[PDB]
Image 1 (tube, helix red, strand yellow):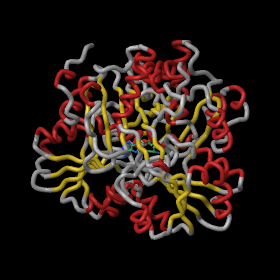
Image 2 (cartoon, helix red, strand yellow; image 1 turned 90 degrees about the vertical axis):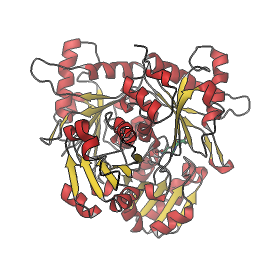
Image 3 (tube, helix red, strand yellow; image 1 turned 135 degrees about the vertical axis):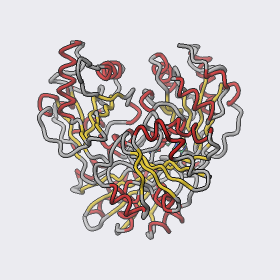
Image 4 (tube, helix red, strand yellow; image 1 turned 135 degrees about the horizontal axis):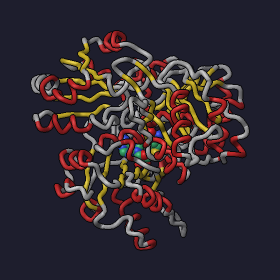
Length: 265
Length: 265
Ligand SMILES: Nc1ncnc2c1ncn2[C@@H]1O[C@H](CSCC[C@H](N)C(=O)O)[C@@H](O)[C@H]1O
């Protein structure tokens, strides 16, 4: 009689919470989407094995246009689960699906899972110091998205770090790298010339958070822009003014140049 | 030779991820800290029973002053687990513990878990619009801290939401309520009179996130300040201008008054 939004986590099938697993195991039917993010350390097969259920994967069109036609109808007579990577309601539009559920007379419940949005804490940057977040979208045709640039500018002026979700085209199997995001930002810099992102700008890259050996690197764009950070997914962070302990972590754990230890107060 | 930082999640013993539980089980010794926060929906007894290991609780001083004397020594000839509520490294002091592990020649790995920082997405508010975060601390003696007030101002000034962690006396198990938090904020507004928090300010309250029955309420201070939001923990959010989709969710899912569709959008 109910619908469950259950997050699967950051990297592999085991990043689901015990709560999430126990509930999914007792659902009559399980649905899922794998276009909002990329779980690089697992396969649908492994998720199905762990949950002991067959999972019907939905596309963005299935969800965005027919969620109330494919999923909700079954709720009235079943306990249904809808699985998604990371946390189901973070940097997605899935929250709106709950409204669709309500209007359809279906109760819904949300089971959280580790999200890239808080996992950035592994970079050593104070979570509270993060300001507005943004997404670096692939330019398409004559349309070249550039709003994320201004977001970085506003946060920096306030001494806040900027979290940059990188773009994804799940059906084309394209996952934007930190390198590609940097290239786009350098280009937007030439455009606006606001001195927001250049060769000397310090950045932090977090790749495959959730795995046991994520790639955590910090340095100047000029040096990291052509560095190999491994397989996707990637996230890119542009730090604001650094606290001393933040810098120490970047140097000790993320291999940043020792010179950032010298914070300019 | 290894140390694992494992998040316990949001509310109860099932909020740990399958990865964290399976790893905690293969660990020779397991420590835990409950001073950055508490797991309001469970007990040490239940967590121990789920993991099947005796758990040694460490106080703030144990960790901040003797982490390398209590935890790291065992981490040399054993696999050690250090459990924390939420997602590891979200608490600002945790990050350096990894530097200590390095200094001691001990490998460390982080096992993520749901954090309130990402769980607020269940309020229906877009995660990207959250700005800097703050903690509302209890005034004591001749000390009246109000930086959290300024944080709201700067965020809402740029149309961003403000996540407010409420004070907590971990050791004494005392939780600051949203009600008290609103009272404090009304007192500060009467102090700085910068028009940031009044009876007409729209706020959002999230209680017991992670539970299947969290309390999600939205409304104007005058109507919520004396409302009973249930048992702790409470989280207070002061939203900035709302996207129609955010407002509709607050009305449909959190019982917000229709007035917000015209006043806060
Ligand atoms: N494990 C991971 N490591 C690095 N970046 C990740 C990641 N998981 C997601 N992302 C980043 O976030 C984007 C997906 S946005 C959706 C996020 C998801 N709900 C969550 O809670 O994590 C990706 O394109 C990528 O840039």
